Length: 131
Length: 131
Length: 131
Length: 131
Ligand code: HEC
Ligand code: HEC
Ligand code: HEC
Ligand code: HEC
View 1 (cartoon, rainbow over the protein chains, first blue to last red):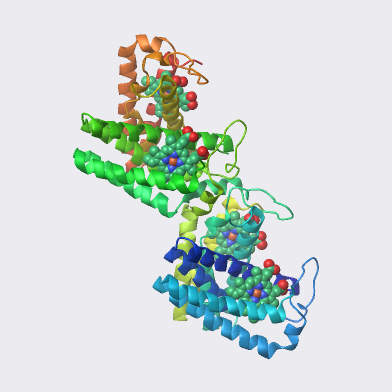
View 2: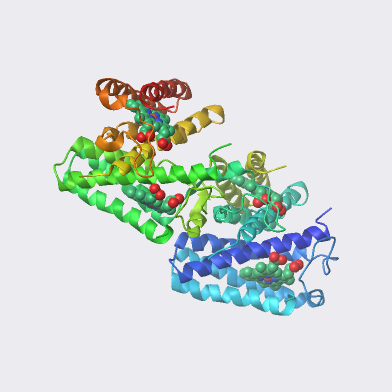
């Protein structure tokens, strides 16, 4: 037995929430006093989570609120699995690049790579996440 | 500016929950049909989250339940934290050097070492101590 | 099980105040008649207090005035703290090793590395997480 | 001509209070799980403060409450500088030994050394500190 539908929703939400925190740290470093190690660590989280196979957390029965757990996934997500697949793979590429650039310590290159990742997060949300 | 106490608790819980999911995947691979890439991806999440600086999510209002958010942290946890920030590290280094130089008895070297310590006191105050 | 928030604020203020007195003695020696033993003793206080783990005095509930005790700490200070405890260091080391071993693809080595990580999770929970 | 009487009282109280905190940490380590580095850092504070020349903080108008500042020094202190001398030398010797033993990491040598320091604190208080 795998994760229940409720567990799948909770778990995917956790991964997203934790990526969001790390994105926020990168933004803070870019706008304030840049800490290269801190940005590298944050970028490594985003890449690792992007590569963690979160598609497995969108099993049958996770399209609607379950128990006391509410989901913000739009029903269209499940009917567009081929496109969700494409965007997820694109997000992986962007996240990998952000980690690579972050390891160099170059804030200006990170700023560009950070923007590309942000655009991938946003593209998926526009299509598949309820406001 | 930063995460509210509620957001800090939610975010640390998210990181832990997501590690738990990835640990479970490793266990499943070890007990069943081993998928090397899957285990590698899961292990990378655990390492990235372990290195993500979650100490920043254990701020002063987060020892007790907040709003609708409940925490399971014990108060004993917090005393193991230390300021690992840039200025603190500058200060410790500078203070250690001042003691070393002072042991030599050389006033001119002490004067220089003393100035470096004073600058660290002042720089922390300017940023983190109210006037 | 430790210092109250009020006691923590009082104690950290005491350490800072006492460092201030010793800094003043060093300054006086530099500007007047230099006493090497006196400067060495003062510098030793500054180094010892810098190394004394005052992070343990920045616990939850010490970000604001308590009782009749007033604090001048800014809320921004706290996010720079990290768990430097034994179990955290064991965990990070174990997690890094699990990722390394997982990259080799060798399931028997992963099984061992996975167990070491699991033991670190569990040991922190036993001490610091409510059942 | 230096620290005001109020500043002298405040400063000596700060040094004592901070030593007290560090003594309490050594006691906590002995009553719980022993952390050698933590005990070493605490012992170093006690030795440094013992050696810091706090006699200079017992200037003329500091035998009584001043302004808003209250003191617990007994009048006998100022008229018994020879015995205060003896106890201070017993204390500095004991504190130096505690730091030495603490650096070895040997808890048994520490518990014993800790007791000798505590006896010196207590003997001065009995004679020269108001209950
Ligand atoms: C699809 C391909 C996505 C990508 C890439 C990213 N996100 Fe996402 N996000 C997605 C969905 C379908 C959902 C809803 C999940 C649910 O079941 O409710 C989300 C949700 C979030 C959230 C809110 C999580 C919560 O607290 O409930 C956040 C904060 C979030 N997403 C952030 C985020 C970031 C920072 C991304 C890239 C770095 C990212 N998302 C990518 C779908 C997808
Ligand atoms: C301290 C050094 C810890 C280590 C190492 C790990 N965990 Fe932990 N865990 C810790 C605390 C203090 C808490 C309570 C957090 C709170 O604010 O409530 C937790 C909690 C968890 C949880 C529950 C999260 C939730 O949904 O509320 C899980 C699932 C969890 N921890 C798992 C986990 C795993 C898998 C670890 C190692 C791989 C791990 N923890 C390490 C403290 C610490
Ligand atoms: C951060 C990295 C700091 C360093 C390094 C030093 N100080 Fe500090 N100082 C700091 C804070 C956040 C505060 C406020 C503490 C509070 O809870 O109110 C202080 C305060 C002081 C004070 C006033 C203490 C009082 O009686 O209220 C003094 C006199 C002081 N600091 C001196 C001092 C000296 C001499 C330092 C280096 C040798 C030093 N500080 C370093 C933060 C930090
Ligand atoms: C004389 C030779 C002393 C030795 C040795 C120690 N102490 Fe002391 N202590 C002494 C005096 C005269 C006073 C009163 C000072 C005043 O002006 O009020 C004190 C006070 C303390 C206090 C209370 C300080 C406060 O917050 O107001 C503490 C906590 C304290 N002393 C602790 C202490 C410790 C831990 C010692 C050895 C390790 C120690 N004292 C030695 C005189 C002397």
